[PDB]
Length: 60
Length: 60
Length: 60
Length: 60
Image (cartoon, rainbow over all chains, first blue to last red; front, side):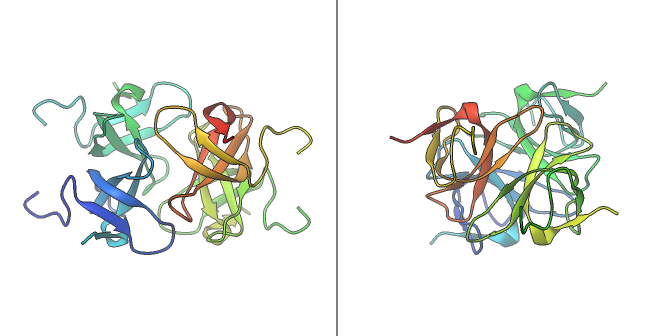
């Protein structure tokens, strides 16, 4: 999107707390989370978790 | 999207099993769920659940 | 349990952020969340969310 | 429990669809899922998902 932090296919991980890592497969927006992403785990195919942008970091 | 069953803001509910109802706030796609939606509950603001298109119906 | 903050059937709600309210239906424990509860929403029968004890408050 | 299919610490996996594998860390019961388990992924420490007994199999 002309503005999003990440794009479909970006490989990301959660920065802290419970772990999660995999590819960006989607997106969501609410008043509480105005920029959120859906992420399919690379260890467990098919399982997707949603998180706010702040919780995620791209993997370099 | 030039093709999606639902659009942001559509009011939907789960057709069966565990209940869920509210507005479409997002979208996701995986091999397992090639057309999925994120839905923020209208009863519990801020809480979003993700589901495959098949599980949802627009509320008329 | 001879020690738990809440019991099955306790009516609770999330204290802040995304909302959630309903009855305690279960329990879990990990290193990250050594005291956690499963809660079935009272607005959406059948839908359960899990949270750490800290996030919940009994409803008086 | 004098009756449960699995016990805390059992190593299990989801039988089909989205994958999930790890240890049993908890339990829940609703009318919809009268026997459910919380499972912490062994690939993503700290992340727990809940499922009905039917969806899981112990790993031998």
